[PDB]
Amino acid sequence: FRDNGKHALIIYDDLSKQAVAYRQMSLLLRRPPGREAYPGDVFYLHSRLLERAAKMNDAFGGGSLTALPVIETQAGDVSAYIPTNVISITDGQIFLETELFYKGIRPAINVGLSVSRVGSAAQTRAM
Amino acid sequence: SSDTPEGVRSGAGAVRDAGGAFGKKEQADEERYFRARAREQLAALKKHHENEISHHVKEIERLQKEIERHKQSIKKLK
């Protein structure tokens, strides 16, 4: 749909269960492990999947592809191995907490830690 | 640390989960205060008037039985 001038959207639910299904294939093929028994190329696994999302120009068709990956942390620690690979690849995060979910705020988006680095250049003039 | 998404940040309800000095000073202050409120709410709960009447009678019945005993004692002696 990007190659033929159309628009698209994709949702990976979720990317933290692909790094686990790939670690099992590595350690059964006897590859050298690394941090948390992940191989040396788990950064190269997620980078060449998210870099395929692009905004093409008018000489090629004007298509697009938008990518929303889901990542599950454990006890809110984003400083793990896979929660730091996919954070440094993408643009901004939406950080849903569990404390605000029971205090009444639903959807529980924390806007203190959520950013977007395309900024205000994707909003309409009214909004 | 906390002035980024990466670093450690504290949530709500972290003094009791630690279980230290302030975590024990908080549990014995919620109990020594709500012990006196089980006194004032229970002492004023005895001020139901219908219970006092019922108790005006149980006592009466008890006393009437004692009188009955005495009356029988007299009957015998006579």
Image (cartoon, helix red, strand yellow):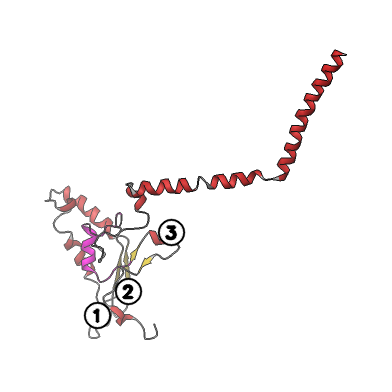
Where residue B46 appears, as percent x and y from the top left, is 65, 43
Which of labels 3 and 2 is toward the front?
3
Where residue A81 appears, as percent x and y from the top left, is 20, 57
Q: Which segment did they paint magenta? A: A73-94
Mark 2 closeness class: few <14, some 14–19, many ≥20 residues within 10 Å: few
Please say if the residues under marks 3 and 1 sit with CB atoms less than 8 Å apart.
Answer: no
Between the residue at mark 3 and the residue at mark 1, the CA separation in whole angstroms equals 42 Å
The residue singled out by tag 2 in the image is A8
The residue singled out by tag 1 in the image is A56
Amino acid, disc 1:
Met
For image coordinates 17% across by 51% down, the residue present is A26
Question: Which picture quadrant has residue B66?
Answer: top right
Question: Which picture quadrant has residue A108?
Answer: bottom left
- Name the quadrant of the N terminus of chain A: bottom left
Where residue A34 appears, as percent x and y from the top left, is 14, 52
Please say if the residues under marks 1 and 2 sit with CB atoms less than 8 Å apart.
Answer: no
Disc 1 element = loop
Q: In this view, does A47 lie to the left or right of B34?
A: left
